[PDB]
Amino acid sequence: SDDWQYEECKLSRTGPPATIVAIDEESPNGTVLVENMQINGRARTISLSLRDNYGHWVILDPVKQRLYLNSTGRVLDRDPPSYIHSIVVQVQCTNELVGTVILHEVRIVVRDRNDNPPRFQQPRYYVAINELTPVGTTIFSGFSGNNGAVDIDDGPNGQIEYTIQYNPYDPTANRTFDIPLTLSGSVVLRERLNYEEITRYLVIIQANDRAPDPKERLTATTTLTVDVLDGDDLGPLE
Amino acid sequence: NQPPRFQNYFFQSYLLIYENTPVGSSITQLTAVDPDGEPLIFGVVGEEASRFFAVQENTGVVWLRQPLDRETKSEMQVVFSVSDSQGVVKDTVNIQIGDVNDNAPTFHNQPYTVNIPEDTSVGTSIFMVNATDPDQGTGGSVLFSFQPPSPFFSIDGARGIITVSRLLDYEVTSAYQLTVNATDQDKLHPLSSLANLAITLSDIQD
Ligand SMILES: [Ca+2]
Ligand SMILES: [Ca+2]
Ligand SMILES: [Ca+2]
Ligand SMILES: [Ca+2]
Ligand SMILES: [Ca+2]
Ligand SMILES: [Ca+2]
Ligand SMILES: [Ca+2]
Ligand SMILES: [Ca+2]
Ligand SMILES: [Ca+2]
Ligand SMILES: [Ca+2]
Ligand SMILES: [Ca+2]
Ligand SMILES: [Ca+2]
Ligand SMILES: [Ca+2]
Ligand SMILES: [K+]
Ligand SMILES: [K+]
Image (cartoon, each protein chain N blue to C red):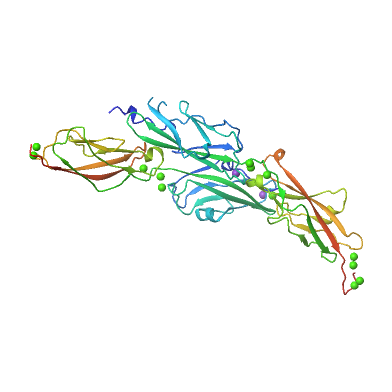
């Protein structure tokens, strides 16, 4: 026994059997994924090929022991519709001395980029409110749920903060209404309404996502049209 | 009020858990900063995630409920939550289950029997065993040997092919009971199994 030849095809690094790497989605064609696989031997004391390589996302250079991203034609998209969270291939090492075959799994974990803005599911929003509505009432909840802004990214990159912006064509909209919690989007009445003074407000509503770095955050805006309906009471108010 | 933000590295890459991690172990501890200094409430989100992971609300200590098996699943997209008085922040963690060598080789097609004439030439192939092992890389590459070794038969280490070594003789030995060992090539903790091999010989008139 000279063991110098059973040890071909094993790994000369440490850590887990699988070789795990993170890379950004929509990486450019040719991106290095694995620099060196760190397999003992010489692709001639061995030979290397790829199995389980669907859509040929990985190219192999055997001599270097180096995986490249095959991307010409298309983009590596993690977001819907594509949903490419990760790519798994096998690097097959045929040992050319003793005959062993070993499979070295490679798992590419594809990282989300803030490459998508919030998009309102409606072109515009609307509510009609009687003027007898009590101050403090939650007069609109439609930006909560799935009918407000939607952002197809992951985590903070896909999570929405709602605010009321100053409308110069309607300065009192943002003083009469408030979104007290930016993550809910609930709109609350701050001031008593008055049909006989103002019957309509155009409330400009902004949605930004919450990418960690503020320079990379994206935006959408819509209008919430509040019509005021005339209120009458048995008592002495209207 | 500004919302909380998670701080742990693994929202930025992945988190490695070995499949042998015992139930009740601490995987990790969620960390979050709130600009307002207020107290935070940590949790997990998702039907699947909650069955495997529990999260203590105040510390953000994640522990394992059910056991992990790399042979069933090697990836999980898990969602964690952290909450202040104004609402909930969620981020996803790519969890990778690291392989350990916890399976031994399984011999297939047993039992193994052979019937050959005593006048079988040296060099002749007379059987082939086969085994598999579900572990990754070295833990699932199998080597075959006889244990104890035989002066009359040998087995190829990688392919499991059995050949005649020396000339046979029915008048001396009409039958052999051999043991094949199948070992994985796991460097640290290698695992093995045994299969019987019955070589009966048939008589020529010589
Ligand atoms: Ca994308
Ligand atoms: Ca994205
Ligand atoms: Ca986004
Ligand atoms: Ca009135
Ligand atoms: Ca009235
Ligand atoms: Ca009245
Ligand atoms: Ca009246
Ligand atoms: Ca806060
Ligand atoms: Ca297992
Ligand atoms: Ca295993
Ligand atoms: Ca094994
Ligand atoms: Ca004889
Ligand atoms: Ca005879
Ligand atoms: K993440
Ligand atoms: K505090």
